[PDB]
Image (cartoon, rainbow over all chains, first blue to last red; front, side, top):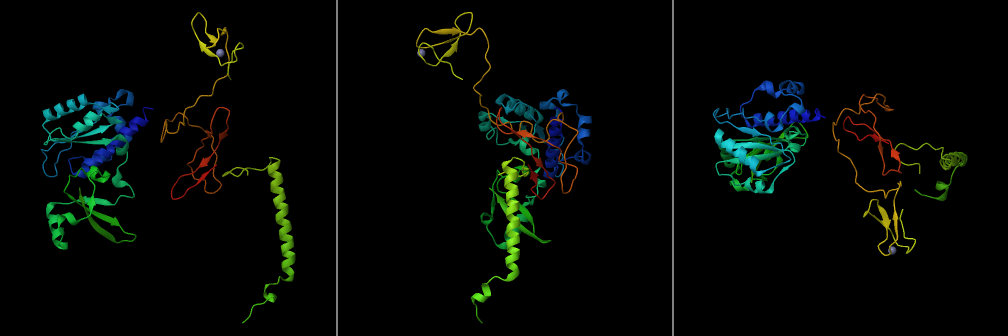
Length: 209
Length: 50
Length: 107
Ligand SMILES: [Zn+2]
């Protein structure tokens, strides 16, 4: 004990950071290849480490298009997150003056906060991931073909090519694990590059509903 | 072209081989059942003795 | 194991209402105080402890000696054993091997 939990912490940090990079926010390469021993060097052993704070991260910004757009990552400690804790998180958020933030739950989170997690504000939205899921980054799994998001012009050209109306494309569910990974909203489009049985590749497009 | 019982009658050496083989199998069959019922049989590491 | 009243042949329960616990009947005033101890239970029931230490669990159960395969003998399948059902029930030993693209696991 105190070694498996630290391994979990390092792994979840690695995967979440990979997701931040993939979404295109600011990130430093030297931290991408951070080792577990490096994590021990930069953070003490489990008994000496405080879960609700130690891992909190907000360095990532949307430097891809706007370095001024900061983003916040939180890691509660209680097995089920409570209303008061998210109220503290939301007041801290308002103090920081940001739009969105990510939350990592250990085991669950209370039903009243389940309901609140859809209607905090039109201008603010929150995204919750399970520790269990984050332990592995699905993007690397063998059975998940590469997904890519594209700009509105690309979809314009595509729909012009086949002479289609947007609502004719194949669908992809919003709650899909990959859709959650990419944090994409309804009405976007996704390209897929299925690895053929041979060197070839097949391209197909799916819409998020 | 024809088929007749001359074409499905066993030959000489077949009798002898069949006799010897059938003997062999039965002795081995006896040996295994004796090893089991005495408990000396070595359980195969994928199933029970039976 | 069950207890029954000599006076009425019915099952006995255990209760305390004085300095010492007793077996007593709920039909007749027969009572038998228990001044000493007895050593047989009802064999209670709780389910299978499977993944309490799943995955790469604590490292305190390392051991020195291990067996080997008859085919390839690559370096990674150190021993484990386990149990079947219950206190008076037997134990079973298996041997399982997992590199990739196969299904091997011996008994
Ligand atoms: Zn009675």
